[PDB]
Image (spheres, rainbow, N blue to C red):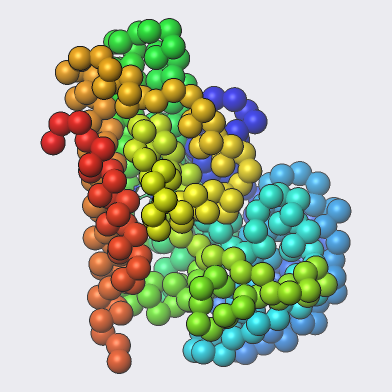
Amino acid sequence: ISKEYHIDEEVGFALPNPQENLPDFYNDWMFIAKHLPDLIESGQLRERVEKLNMLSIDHLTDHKSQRLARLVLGCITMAYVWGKGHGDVRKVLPRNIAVPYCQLSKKLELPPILVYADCVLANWKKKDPNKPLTYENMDVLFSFRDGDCSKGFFLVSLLVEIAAASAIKVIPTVFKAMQMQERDTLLKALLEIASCLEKALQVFHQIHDHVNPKAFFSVLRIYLSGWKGNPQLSDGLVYEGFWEDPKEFAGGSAGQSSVFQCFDVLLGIQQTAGGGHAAQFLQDMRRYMPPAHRNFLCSLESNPSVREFVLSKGDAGLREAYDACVKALVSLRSYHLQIVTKYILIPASQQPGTDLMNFLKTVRSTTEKSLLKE
Ligand SMILES: Cc1nccc(N2CCCc3nc(C4(NC(=O)c5ccc(F)cc5)CC4)ccc32)n1
């Protein structure tokens, strides 16, 4: 894969070895983000954010510092807007935080809101550099509240992203085998993708240990919520000293992951085509990815179809290898519906996520119908 797309070998779509600390100029931002559970509970976060001076973004030179500054400012924006998470909400984001955040967001080509690329892909570190990428050795940089299971929720999402990296690196081999006209290399490449997607499902199983249902629904789901089609923030969030009118932006979700879309585009599973609701959302969430990663997904569509290549040739081995990738995806989609039933629906039923289930049923229905043999 080309280096311009920003896909690491082992790490994949995730940012390899992100920065923990910023430079000395951004200590006032870094204090509020590090102690975000403490300042919300005491009722002094909105006091601390309003006290800030408008720090310029010129000292953030390299890419990893800018991604850290997006994560720091993004988490502060969710904490300032939502607050304790008991109805009391802020429509106005102050100039001291909003001006540098929108300027930094415009520079990186992202919306000024916490996305999957901030809170999963950039929000991690390695405890021991010698020891490998696993949950015991890994830890998140920032959290919202105490007992929110943000460590469990974001790292298990990241580990599935890291598991998918082994499938991603062999994508060049698939398109090279089609143009060069090599059946056995194409069959070998597809079985390797199917194997890696099967292993990614076993990594997905770790979410039950590290996250609980009551913690995600009541606490962590509130902070990940955006301001697009929300009864609380109807018109949107006004960013002070940057835009005049309030601009709407959707919150964090699985659809913002490039892993969520790339294998559908590779295998010709028509998610984005056929202008339904689930199609439009997945297309909209490409702008919530980083610019290099949306270009990667878009460049997969430019290459010729793997489905039509496998369909045109009357080859049972290629069809079985193609179906192994699709069946591996259906298993991941099926398992994601079991998580949304456990972590959103059952917590919601015990109080005085229908649209999220209806989305993931439609995404799975598209994946299952794309099978050649049942
Ligand atoms: C191909 C495929 N199939 C099924 C699922 C799938 N992904 C993308 C790779 C990891 C992944 N993680 C989550 C989980 N996390 C989130 O949905 C999530 C939500 C909000 C947020 F701000 C950040 C992450 C763990 C619940 C769901 C789907 C998938 N990818």
Q: Examine the rendered structure and indicate whether residue 119 appears above or below residue 303.
A: below
Quarter where residue 141 is shown: bottom right
| Residue at figure coordinates x 63%, y 43% from the top left | 291
| Residue at figure coordinates x 49%, y 30% from the top left | 300
* Quadrant (top left/top right/bottom left/bottom right) for the C terminus: top left
Q: Position of residue 301 (x, y in %)?
A: 48, 32
Work out whether residue 331 or residue 148 is closer to the camera in this orientation and state it. Answer: 331
Q: Examine the rendered structure and indicate whether residue 271 appears above or below residue 40.
A: above
The residue lying furthest to the left in this view is 374
* Quadrant (top left/top right/bottom left/bottom right) for the N terminus: top right
Let me know if residue 336 appears in the view: no
Work out whether residue 95 or residue 214 is closer to the camera in this orientation and state it. Answer: 95
| Residue at figure coordinates x 28%, y 43% from the top left | 367
Q: Examine the rendered structure and indicate whether residue 36 appears above or below residue 140.
A: below
Q: Position of residue 233 (x, y in %)?
A: 57, 80
Seen in the image, is 77 located left or right of residue 333?
A: right
Seen in the image, is 272 located left or right of residue 120?
A: left
Work out whether residue 42 or residue 86 is closer to the camera in this orientation and state it. Answer: 86
Let me know if residue 359 appears in the view: yes
| Residue at figure coordinates x 70%, y 81% from the top left | 92
Quarter where residue 45 is shown: bottom right
Q: Position of residue 98 (x, y in %)?
A: 75, 70
The residue lying furthest to the front in this view is 275
How many badges with numbers are in the image? 0
Q: Position of residue 228 (x, y in %)?
A: 54, 70
Ligand 1 appears in which quadrant? bottom left
